[PDB]
Image (cartoon, rainbow over all chains, first blue to last red; front, side):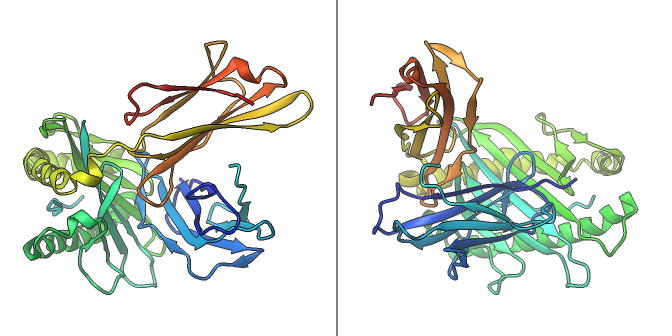
Length: 99
Length: 9
Length: 276
């Protein structure tokens, strides 16, 4: 009984180039609770990433929010890398400002 | 306000 | 209107890497307000919402006492569970718990919860009458017989209808500014062409509180489920939530579609139509 994480990478506020915002990675619907979540800037791990306290939904599946303060630009590509026991390899989800 | 969770399975 | 209080705890064994980690979190509706982590340095129940800091020093001592006792109980329960399912002592196992209550607009008791899950699967749950147990499998059936004979549910019932409701009531008042607010969603529609024949319409709902919301697509005023994509409601990180609903439409037919947004912060549901 192991469930794979759903992943959403998005900003707190509508992205404007040159303005401070928050880059979020929402992982949910997973089991067991151990999970590896990084936020990447141009393929490189962002260092000061905070996360929410381990919690869960009605169906007992876990969720976490990983977030970092950032300033989007036109060049800079942001992503979230996720690893879990259910994944054969880490899953990379690119930040799409329209999603 | 938390509950007293004392009983065993 | 109606309000809830929930406590969620997770105990995860890690054989060879010391005792199980215990993490507990408390929520009023969709606002977290406390946490306890057995691996943290403080060894105290910690505040996670500004309005819970107005509780006196005796609350933090009492609540720390309670969450530490639950930490010890669920460590034992992890051992009892191995024995019941005849599992190896070397593997990693998970014991989760949820308890709490639901109150009306008058701050009066509506429903109570007290339930376990072992390795992400329903173990034992207190039924709505607060007198009986829903045991899911054979192992849970053993606990059920033990708890029914010892009349344990009366202790749950006294908590859920009393202490739970009083705490929830006091929290709603102390954090009125936060918890009793309604942040309606800020809505908008975007257009994204696929081919010369197809386009995606994405209906957005942002900055809303509480988390409950419904987004629906209709074509010619008739409900539309086909060609629809709905993401899970997600936290913005500032205490508000976000969600979007999308539909793949034929080109030139965009304006026949409408997005319907239901939120308790709204005086009426909003209807959105693509307007180039």
